[PDB]
Image 1 (tube, helix red, strand yellow):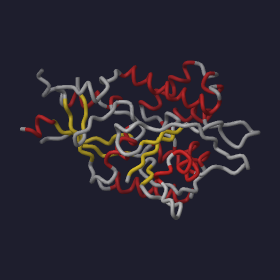
Image 2: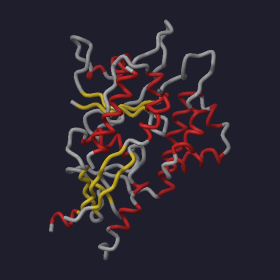
Image 3: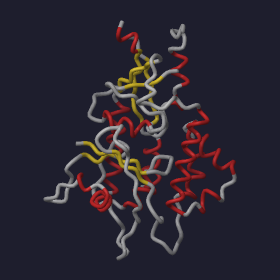
Image 4: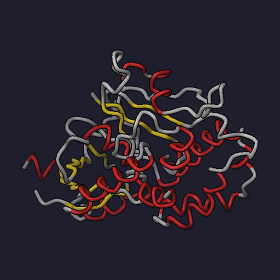
Length: 20
Length: 262
């Protein structure tokens, strides 16, 4: 669960910040 | 691992495009990168300026026929109203015909600060019978607030770490400061009294919480999810330690705000 939380946050960051 | 979880909660962002209702009805926008854990009014002196020139002639925000509340944190607002929506976020700006019936008058900066400290206090009440925050000289409260306002992560957590400690003899906090928002923003949030650990010493999991206070989000067949359970834009596993969740993915106002979406 911890690794899922960290990774999911990683990916969240990437979509929303990366693109723009 | 944990410190990075905290940094990446703090710095989560929402790309946002403010456009004018009167430019849309007549559309040059203002682009910004809103901090997920802040509040509208806190970072909308800037917006007031940008369009203040065009304000030849009391400014509120809206999204698809829905006013946006000045005291819900930005990130929760996005998650709850427009997670599935395509980015950047399209916020309509209205400075005419304020919705007094369906919106609170725009708070000052000090009035938000009031709400923020009031929430922090309602949180430390449930966590430590207010023993931790009370101890803090006023200057510490101000350091918390200015660390939020100026995106100073280090400054803010220098003080918040105390508020996330608990006694050695116990396995967590007293209760968990949490709020659960369901179908829409105008639907009241939910807040209840829940302990981090059950009688048997077992640490409680988010799944336990939703089963107790919000079972409509649980498929009664497999005990798994029926709807989306979003926190800071992600969906943690129903078997995640609530104590840990509170310690690490609360908003700076020490609450676990939790959006629920069908």
